[PDB]
Image (tube, rainbow over all chains, first blue to last red; front, side):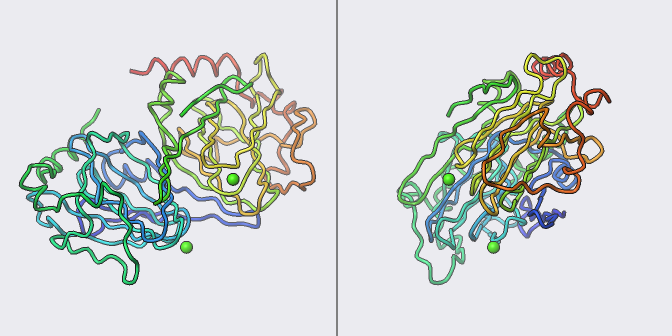
Length: 200
Length: 200
Ligand SMILES: [Ca+2]
Ligand SMILES: [Ca+2]
């Protein structure tokens, strides 16, 4: 199994191996040892969440306030979603950049470190996503940026009408969140990553 | 969400809540905070494994050598399995007892602490089980007892022919493992549980 960086620093793609035989398959979907080798730290699992989404449901762009924010390891267990990581970190060389990854097989997982924005859209009806998070979900620490903001310009799938929740529909754009001081700061994100590597 | 003990000390049933709306559902499938409240410790997640099994495939009865053995939080994400926890602990008041739980919905999960034996049979073709484990899988520390041993007398489902791997077919019975000193000791299991509660 491999874990390699994506184009936004802090996002990683994990490709995991299937051992198959006549009885079915075994897969190591998540390995703390593999993550510590790639990242320098074990993110820990405080919560595992599962979300079932109707086709075209767009969940995002969400992030937890830093610190400690939430790091996420995301896998689509059935069906397919288009996952988009967004660099919401002010002062980042790639601030406002995004990258889309198709998660359409259980052997591909996305790791998003603390301080990045995460989103996905369900490409199939009732797509199931599981995600491990380093910190428990807390509504009070949870923030959102509108996923269709033209200031981000995410290329959501052609031909699928997005379905947003009330909360995601009324979410501010990135430029509003920026000037209100509600986005993470890139140097604070880097220092947090270094702190995790030093724990002990 | 609730987490309550089963009939074998060390096995627990977790029932988790679904928040459903027109867009799908959100579920908190695993909560370290909930586990620490029930158990006195956070087991930690070293690995998440996923197994797909043909109908009638019987995986088990498996256990990792104590210590540190492996604690397992098991959920059937799709289809149905019959999970059987076995009290393999010599000196236990319930040594050789077992309990079957039908895992046929993603909102029910079984927690098996370090030192118990775990098994399941797939009731549907291609049933998918995910499980979180406190320690990484290591073949050298992994042991097995034959799941059809009449000395355990597990009531596997009526009308389904069991399909075992070569390794599970050639697995010894519980009485052989006992006299060869390959089963966990109940007082060692209890002392290990107390050690986890004292860590810090
Ligand atoms: Ca697929
Ligand atoms: Ca069901």
